[PDB]
Image (cartoon, rainbow, N blue to C red; front, side):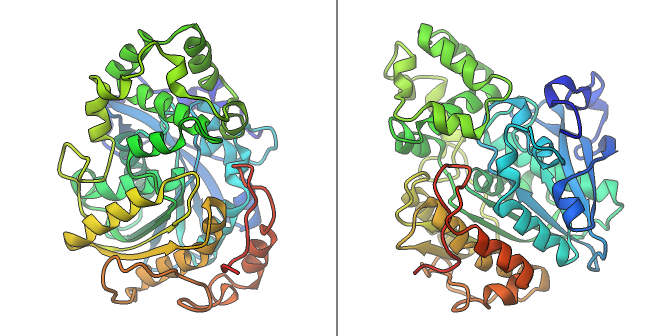
Length: 431
């Protein structure tokens, strides 16, 4: 690609004086060429910045920012969370965004991603997309992801000298929605100066344990194994515990899914029908320490959580396929119901006839319309959590209205194309 592999690059390392940097402070930066930047006439940069890991240690991370040619004003910031879904360093969103064709997780940066970021740039928003898994590629580590993201937003504001109360909105789907929900949950306690006016996410994994039990042994069991790997990379005592229990197969397999160049496509293709329990000599792992208690922290479902989960009060749009076959629907419905009973402002859109990839599209125009309204202060008053399928042209303006013809024609082109997950996208509205 336009830069070396991140494994080969000291830009992806944490300097020994990391602790002297404030949260979100820019350590170094570099101009980078990106497909999205070239397509939208927006300069792109990578920012190496300070953040905080799960063990509350100061670490560096990388984020990618795009500067609109005609910024809206006052300045508005759009944080887009990618479904990286891998535990290797070179699967990073920053690397995947570069001009180039050999990046192993390139797929996660093309397809719907450029539509969404392109759209945000055409509205005049500053765009940031952080490498939310951080330098350990700790997929699904929520505190890891939440802090990295909030600190990436901080870094864009520092880098561009944006006003402190610059409006912020956040968006993501699938693994990017786990990252998004975690960043919203931590905003209050970790980054309360960020003026977040909205957030929009779909296909949300809210409980690590629940997403695990739904996935294990099925067609997308590679995602279960990726979560085990990613969580162990954020929790050292879970890592030791697991290491001690891996049989020879488990040892070969954990190394494999952490191997350079083993990204989402390889996760999907290598592990259908794997039972992660086949990797260990202990079937009761879910119930032992330190795992069981980590699972109670790695959840935003309060019924399951061993801590008081935040309730963001700003407007939110949350969508999900009821028949979701990859990320389970009910845990997310449970999260919305709970949050709504504590004063949240959630417009909830469960799609009764949909699957994971088709709901990725169905909720997209509603999602972006919602974010535009949140920036404008014009999100409609709704009874929190009422299950209403949001349909473009019915509950929102048309695709052409929201996106413009160009971007809506790009969105129509996805219909029937393969997604990162090996299943085709469908149309803008349910048939």
